[PDB]
Image 1: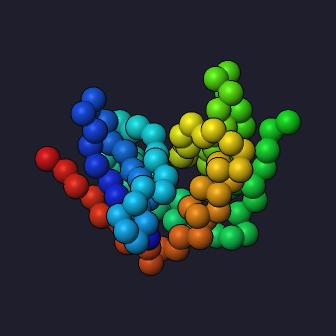
Image 2 (image 1 turned 90 degrees about the horizontal axis):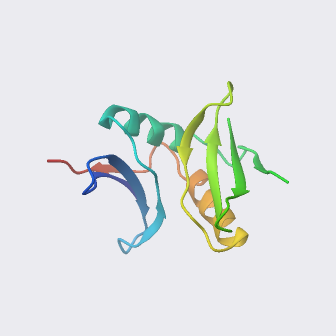
Image 3 (image 1 turned 120 degrees about the vertical axis):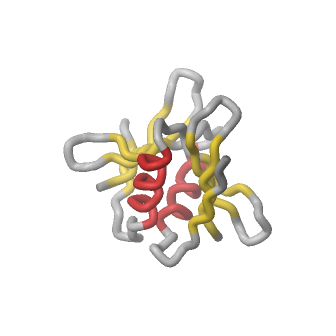
Length: 57
Length: 58
C-alpha cells in the first residue's frame, strides 16, 4: 500500500492510493500547485481510526 | 477533522475531508454504491505516516 503523486494530461496535480500489486484503490481530485497536493496527502495519512465518519441525511 | 459521505445529482456517492472552519481539504471520486465509498474511506484512514509516498513529475 502506497500513495502516488503525479501530473495529469490537463495540467493539474493529483494523487491515488495503490495496493501491493500496483492496483488502484482510490483516486483523488485536482489541485493548483504541487505544494497544496502534498499537504493534502500528509493530512490524510495523519488521519487515525478514531477519525469520525458522518453521513449527510 | 472528519470525513463526510454524501450523494450528488448524478446519483453517485462521494466523500470529503472537512476541517475545523468547514474547509474542504481532500475530495473523493464518484462511487456507484454507498458501500464502496465507505470501504475507500476505511482504507485511507488505515494508512499511517509510515505509508510511502511516491511522486512523479516532469
